[PDB]
Length: 237
Image (cartoon, rainbow, N blue to C red):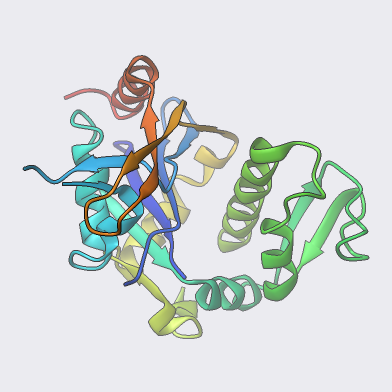
């Protein structure tokens, strides 16, 4: 059971407003996720850009190509993109997820109490989009993002639900693909470590628009740490 990767995407011309790369490994028995910031700078040649805009080129496959260029060593095996509608459905189509909420967030929704809570599509999205209310800042939105993704995955392993979500869901994976994963990599959900690519933001003037835009310069040092980590996650050929 060779380990594999899958680029998780969240949309909303079109853009990839959330980009998460993940690796599952039966041996190591763990999931390794990395959320690359949506503003990550990318060269086109001659013209710079934000990684989230790689969606414009060929839909999702485009972003996949941007993540692979951004991670030369690392190979992206599968991809799965959903817009927010597709998200809401997906959660309900699986009966709603369940997650451990770290902090009292009842000021956003009475259900966002402490401990394990159950959320339906709408409620899950309201959970994930929280911000000011969570004292943990970006890492906070990051945990919550993670929790919902694993919460959705623990349900999936307990299908033709790709009909209830349909058009808002896109994956190069097949039906027999998901099947094999639930029946072989189920264990990989025991250990799940997600982290955010470290770097710095910067304002670089734009010739087309007429002003400075925002870009994220990932730390060259950490980019390798995570690149090699992913290679070690997939057993470098």
